[PDB]
Length: 118
Length: 118
Ligand code: NA
Ligand code: NA
Image 1 (cartoon, rainbow over the protein chains, first blue to last red):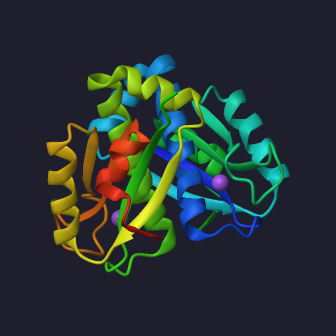
Image 2 (image 1 turned 135 degrees about the vertical axis):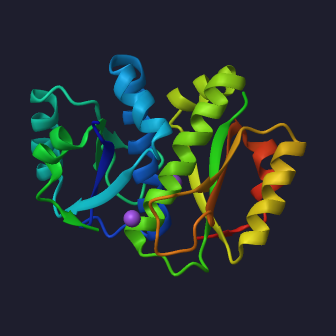
């Protein structure tokens, strides 16, 4: 009776235009979805046919994305920290979003439950 | 020497909040990515390791998404027309975005090249 979800944490301090931010969120969702597909197949499958729920939250620094990624790693959650070579309006290698999940909602919330909604 | 990309067409007439629109764009990207993975594996693989380029464009009606989906189908392009049962702020079954690709840029552009950027 587990519910599954993916939470994408987007940086709101990069002054990115909406189309670019949406693209970054999509990079995170796709990348983490494939991470789950290959190493947590059951979680991926359940999520994918139960609405593939996604919630977009935000942070105001690059540092918070790294700390959240570390927490996701420590809990064994599929995740993807995104950088985009094509996003030249920000410095090369700058991370834009962190996608966490798909995974059981209660586990994902341990990492992202207190983040604020975009 | 083919370049690959995925274009996600989002409806800008639904008055959706940014977090929800980004989530819908992500649904499209993930769904179409898996469509390509299963029926155009080569296109998916190239795209996925070459930056998985995504561009977000918009339309102002549900009707345009259907016409674009038909065009994508006629050109044999992986695509995903999205509806979200959890998006209750709009009528049930309402389509929100159409993701086209990954596929060679020149083919994708035949469908989305004249759409305006979000
Ligand atoms: Na660019
Ligand atoms: Na909802």
